[PDB]
Amino acid sequence: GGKAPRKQLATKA
Amino acid sequence: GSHMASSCAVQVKLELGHRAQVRKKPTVEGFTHDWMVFVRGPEHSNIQHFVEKVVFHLHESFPRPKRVCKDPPYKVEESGYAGFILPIEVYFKNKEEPRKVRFDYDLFLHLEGHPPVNHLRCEKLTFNNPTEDFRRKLLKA
Image 1: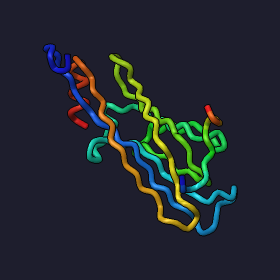
Image 2: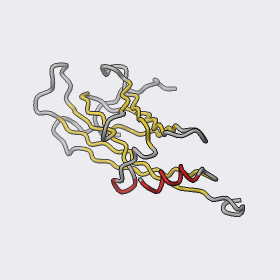
Image 3: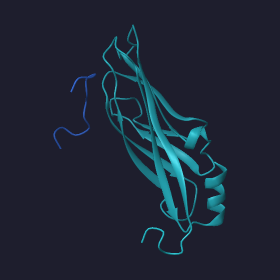
């Protein structure tokens, strides 16, 4: 989308 | 059979919210944002009557990812740079049905120098055939 950066807990899971 | 059986159920409510501010000068760890997450009661009612302790599972990048709050307002005030799904578990003090809840809440933030973030959420807890003492706690909150 369009917001602040994101560090997901599980990469593509 | 929703309300079809002669069962007395009590319904409570918890609030998951957070405000996210940026800093014009990032902190010592070079984190740009400071967010305060919280779990509250229905209409700002103190929930410590049925709520024992609460926990916010932050990202492992955060010093002590596990924030349990036994003290006054259930809130975490931390600094970071990027948002993530933050699973919140609220503990209750009782010996009946599972005294822990799991609310998946998205901790989102704005770009450094853009409108801050203020998101509130209200979740209902429904307990079928609880003990009167527990109702008394759910009502007193």
